Image: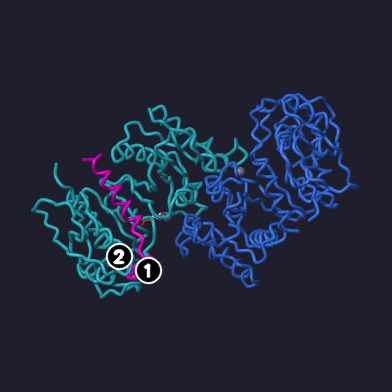
Chain colours: A cyan, B blue
């Protein structure tokens, strides 16, 4: 075997991302942590946190080495303008996107085994003149993936979303057999390839409350969800549902499920989030490479102040690492 | 101070209601338990269950006495036909309705401090030729309430819904400024008068994911929810602005709030039910009196078995009692 490299994008410079990566670095890792950011950004934020940091250069033509405590490997990307923790600078929006692109191309070219992302501020990137709606869409497009699936996990409890950031009013018409097929196909695929689960068991939420309670509250279950599920069950897929979302999240269901598929954003994320603020991991399924992420914002207000909380970033990294085994 | 009386309606005679009430009786209570039902029904179901039961008559002229274990106070209403657990008899629909009317009237008279309802089967009542649009609708209409708001609580969390059992595709257009003002006024009002919370703190969910994030994920927050909340805040009402549902359910928020207002069914109930479950109690806001209700159905398939589970009924009663204590 060979020591693996993972690429990490701290995210918004003025945000908590660099703070968190400097903190990640205070411990040992079984992989080489290739951080794609500006060297000075990290050096300065480290100082502000009274934390030690020595950076070694990313060297593609030398073997990778596990990351020792107090260090990080650096894939340099220059900042557009000077940084002040907590204050945004539109020009640095190009900087952020650049790190994302480079880290993404590194996973596509096989340079890196996984990609872990810090938080980014969508607003400032747009302000810079760059259409950006989030990492998920960014990688999906740059990776030219047919379709990606957003997942949230806290360990055994994993929730995927059939639809993501759509206005509530657009969800219903979005639930088509075509969409359910791709999403579930990907969910089933990745649970096997990336999560190492031979025969994955997926728990599916209905669209309406009470899963449509017959026909009194919506026809989507009887019209498209149920039919598709049985089309897939015949394909050998182990699927349970559709079930009511406020009943589905129980031991008699979860204990025998490897993942839950929610029809929409606020149907599945609240329970997961209430299951623990930190320790929550964002995962993108459907990409050619493993991509995990923190499950929180840039928290400009905390940047450089040292009240961090690297729990989510650390779990994100541990998961990506554990995931590398199943793919390599 | 003085011992209060609460009225309980076992509900559908053939369902588990009577079973649940006979078990409730096996323990002492700080209030007098007035059960509006047919004596024989209760006596018999007690036999079938191997549980002891002594019924004392409702004596409004006497001082209310806390209920002693193995006993119940009876407000007599006669069945129209013999009851066979697990079998619906249309004729008895008239019985169910009469108990509901009598209990309701008693709550408007001041005879009873609160109403705790057992499960009722709508179908059989309608099949009997009795117009009845639903359990809570009956009390809403008879008490002349203009609007009721459904809430689910567990001692550690209270969640009210702006909309209830509607198809998902109908929620967006239902969230109007009128509905919200009406829903929040009632929620603010009752948190004071029924829960005894002076200066109530309310958390409000946005309709869209990330609360519409600016307006990149929907406009309802900007066009309706935010304007409404602002007006109400102008009246001193403590309202924590529209927060993304997936971040709202967390200590920094919940620990600072008395109630959470969710926009739709699956946005609040899953968290509430994962945070407790059976501990869940349905409270009807908007009526002139306190009304709690079990969380299950008539479950005719369980009546007369012995595997009832008066748990939910107990948390329902316990909750109404507390509400009485904090409002006297
Ligand atoms: N709702 C997701 C979460 O809970 O983290 C978040 O929007 C994902 O954003 P990205 O596409 O930027 O990873
Ligand atoms: Zn999101
Ligand atoms: Zn419901």
Q: Position of residue A158 (x, y in %)?
A: 40, 43
Quick check: can you spot residue B122? no
Disc 2 element: helix
- Residue A96 sits above or below residue B139 on the image: below
Quick check: can you spot residue A253? yes
- B10 or A193, which is in the foreground? B10
Q: Is residue A316 left or right of residue B278?
A: left
- A150 or A133, which is in the foreground? A150
- A276 or B244, which is in the foreground? A276
Ligand 1 within 8 Å, label 1 CB: no
The residue that mark 2 highlights is A19
Q: Main secondary structure of the magenta part?
A: helix
Q: Position of residue A241 (x, y in %)?
A: 49, 34
- Residue B150 sits above or below residue A77 on the image: above
| Sooner in the amino-acid sequence: mark 1 or mark 2 | 2
The quadrant of the image that shows the N terminus of chain B is bottom right
Name which quarter of the figure residue B313 lies in. top right
Name the residue rendered at 65%, 44% in the picture. Answer: B315
- Asked whether disc 1 touches disc 2, contact meaning CB atoms under 8 Å apart, the reply is yes
Q: Chain of mark 1?
A: A
Please state the extent of the stretch shown in magenta in the rendering: A299-328
The CA span between labels 1 and 2 is 9 Å
The residue that mark 1 highlights is A302
């Amino acid at each position: 075997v060979k020591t693996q490299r993972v690429v990490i994008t701290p995210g918004e410079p003025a945000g908590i991302g660099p703070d968190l990566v400097v903190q990640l670095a205070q411990r040992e890792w079984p992989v080489e942590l290739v951080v794609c950011a500006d060297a000075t950004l990290l050096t300065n934020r480290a100082a502000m946190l009274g934390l030690p940091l020595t950076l070694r250069p990313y060297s593609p033509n030398s073997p990778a080495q596990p990351q020792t405590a107090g260090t990080l490997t650096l894939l340099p990307v220059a900042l557009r303008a000077p940084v002040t923790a907590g204050q945004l600078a539109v020009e640095n929006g190009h900087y952020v996107v650049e790190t994302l692109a480079r880290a993404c191309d590194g996973c596509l070219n096989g340079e890196f085994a996984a990609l872990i992302t810090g938080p980014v501020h969508k607003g400032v990137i747009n302000d810079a003149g760059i259409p950006f709606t989030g990492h998920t869409e960014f990688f999906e497009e740059r990776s030219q993936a047919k379709k990606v699936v957003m997942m949230l996990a806290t360990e055994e409890l994993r929730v995927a979303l059939a639809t993501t950031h759509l206005p509530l009013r657009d969800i219903a018409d979005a639930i088509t057999p075509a969409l359910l097929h791709e999403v579930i196909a990907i969910l089933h695929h990745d649970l096997r390839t990336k999560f190492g689960i031979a025969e994955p068991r997926i728990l599916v939420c209905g669209l309406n409350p009470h899963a449509g309670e017959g026909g009194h509250m919506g026809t989507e279950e009887i019209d498209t969800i149920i039919p598709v599920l049985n089309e897939l069950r015949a394909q050998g897929m182990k699927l349970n549902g559709p079930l009511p979302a406020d009943t589905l999240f129980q031991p008699k269901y979860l204990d025998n499920a490897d993942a839950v598929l929610a029809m929409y954003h606020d149907q599945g994320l609240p329970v997961l989030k209430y299951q623990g603020f930190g320790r929550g991991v964002n995962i993108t399924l459907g990409l050619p490479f493993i991509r995990t992420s923190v499950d929180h914002g840039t928290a400009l207000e905390l940047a450089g102040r040292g009240k961090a909380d690297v729990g989510s970033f650390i779990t994100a990294l541990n998961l990506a690492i554990k995931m590398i085994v199943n793919t390599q």
